[PDB]
Amino acid sequence: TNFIRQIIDEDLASGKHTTVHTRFPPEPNGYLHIGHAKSICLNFGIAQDYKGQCNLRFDDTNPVKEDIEYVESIKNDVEWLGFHWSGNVRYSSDYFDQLHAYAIELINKGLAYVDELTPEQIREYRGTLTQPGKNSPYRDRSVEENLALFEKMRAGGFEEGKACLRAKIDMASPFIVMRDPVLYRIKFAEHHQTGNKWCIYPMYDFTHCISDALEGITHSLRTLEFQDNRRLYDWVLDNITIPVHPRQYEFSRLNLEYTVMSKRKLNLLVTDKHVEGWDDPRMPTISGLRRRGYTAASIREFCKRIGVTKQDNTIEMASLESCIREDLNENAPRAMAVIDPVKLVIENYQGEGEMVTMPNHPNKPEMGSRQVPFSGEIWIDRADFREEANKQYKRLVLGKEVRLRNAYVIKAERVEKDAEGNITTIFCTYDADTLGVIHWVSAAHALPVEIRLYDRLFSVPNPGAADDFLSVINPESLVIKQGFAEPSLKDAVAGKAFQFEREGYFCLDSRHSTAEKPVFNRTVGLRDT
RNA sequence: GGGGUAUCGCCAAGCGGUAAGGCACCGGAUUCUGAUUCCGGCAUUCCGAGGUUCGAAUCCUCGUACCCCAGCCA
Ligand SMILES: NC(=O)CC[C@H](N)C(=O)NS(=O)(=O)OC[C@H]1O[C@@H](n2cnc3c(N)ncnc32)[C@H](O)[C@@H]1O
């Protein structure tokens, strides 16, 4: 529960509302990130928990910054997280005629006028955080002039920035938002929904309070930065002819360590080509996390754990990872894969190989078992073999033994190096009947695999606070290794995850996984304390 | 100027009754994944200083730290 749900519990009792109607209003100017997910869970979640409704609305009031590819990807991420919206998808653009009419009502009430102060002059006239603003020389035009002038704007008779429609409120308000905020500005740009029918587009504050009201929204849930805007929201609805008046509630936005959480910065990583795309597995975007191996259920869990409050916060990466581990640890089938392979021959072994049985999930027999090929020439991880090694080292030591996962116990004996003195092959012997512990893969039946290890995109906890966050990108946020996996992964599918025993959770696709050379993304490593 | 928030390393309950939970962490027990699972520990303190009260983190007062607002962006 959170303060917002508590308010709603009250409202229901008193009877202010008998139904709750929320909305998720993203602007299609980029892809959604994990923060947007916190918002999606909140609005859609509250709706379903209270047998209510939640609209998916595209706040598409700025043509030049938006693209149809963004609206497309947003519907996708909302669906993927497991949420359904009310009726058809909505667009603010659906209300452009409506907004135009409401602007005309304000002008008629002398509550709005066409200003001709250039874009620079408006800031010069606006005042400062400590000094009040001053009325524009065009502030007292007659209703008739404003009316004619607005029509000229709409008709395209003014060059961009040469004119705008402003609300007539209070140039001396301590609330900068109330200093005659702009309602409309000129833009000769094609809109992804309205094409070229308009050359004037409504501003955010004007559009949003009216959109909510026409949609019957009961609880407009937004983030803390729109707190000051609150008085403009109510001003507009109080001054036009509209029957409902939605209530606002702000909660703090999500921040995750070692990453950025704004579309502007995420876009720069995309445009400057420092990540493959919005959906790069290293990105905090919904799509990137999906591609990374996270389950929607893991994300919904995360959002449930972090809560909804009014306090600034930065969650630690451990928390998000904990969520994905809790999921995959329970549902992901296990398999063998060697990321850093080194040949190990069993001079003692006789034949072309045999078959050994391995549980698909140890702690869960109900998940079944599989048949895995074993032989005398296998691959183990270079890190699991040491010639010396101290006491705690429970792996393979030149002279000691180690149990090969779900197989036989073997003893290291003769190693073999090359030029630089690197080991090329490890010879051992196996105990005919014997069935630390290391994983392995039979070299003859092994599937050549590309393994992509990922890590924090940035080297610092708060890359957003850097002068140049790009210069603080982590050069090892992605390292590609070529390894070997048990033949069983031959049928692996994109999306589905597996636990590479003693390594971590991995999954296919990665946009690169083909038929010949499979590519696996390490979703997250195993807890190694 | 105006608007917010300050409870254990990171999140977060508590709305006058004398400090939930999660993540992280530190111990021990299981375990053919040094995983998991499993028991145990972890703020006598709630930004600070006063005041009212039988009694406050929860009310009031003065402070202090931090966040947001001066786009014809959202
Ligand atoms: N009052 C409002 O709702 C304004 C919505 C505005 N068009 C907007 O913010 N669009 S947006 O596409 O940028 O984001 C859409 C919603 O996502 C929320 N949001 C954005 N970043 C968030 C974050 N880091 N954590 C939690 N929530 C976050 C916004 O509040 C908005 O409602």
Image: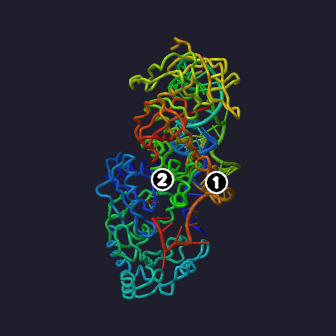
Q: Chain of mark 2?
A: A
Residue A527, position as x, y percentages in the image = 57, 33
Expressed as whole percent of the image width and height from the top left, the position of residue A6 reads: 43, 48
> Which amino acid lies under the numbered mark 1 shown in the image of this protein?
Val
Residue furthest left as drawn: A87
Task: Work out which quarter of the rendered image holds the N terminus of chain A and state it.
Answer: top left
What label sits on residue A472 in the rendered view?
A: 1
From the viewer's perspective, is A256 left or right of A152?
A: right
Choose the circle earlier in sequence order: 2 or 1.
2
- Which callout, 2 or 1, points to the residue nearer the camera? 1
In the picture, which quadrant includes the C terminus of chain A? top right
User: What mark, if any, has residue A33 been given in the picture?
Assistant: 2
Tags 2 and 1 touching, CB below 8 Å: no
Mark 2, ligand 1, within 8 Å: the answer is yes
Q: Quadrant of residue A383?
A: top right
User: Where residue B45 sits: x, y (%)?
Assistant: 65, 41
Q: Nearer the viewer, residue A40 or A232?
A: A40
Residue A281, x across and y down, in percent = 50, 47
Where B2 sits versus A33, above or below? below
Label 1 packing within 10 angstroms: few (<14), some (14-19), many (20+): some
Residue A114 position (above or below residue A34): below
Colouring scheme applied when the structure was drawn: rainbow
Say which quarter of the image contains residue A150.
bottom left
* Viewer-nearest residue: A262 or A411: A411
Q: Which mark is residue A221?
A: none
Classify mark 2: residues with Cα within 10 Å, few (<14), some (14-19) or many (20+): many
Could you say which is closer to the camera, residue A232 or residue A268?
A: A268
Q: Amino acid at mark 2?
A: His
**In this rendering, position of residue A170 left or right of residue A68:** right
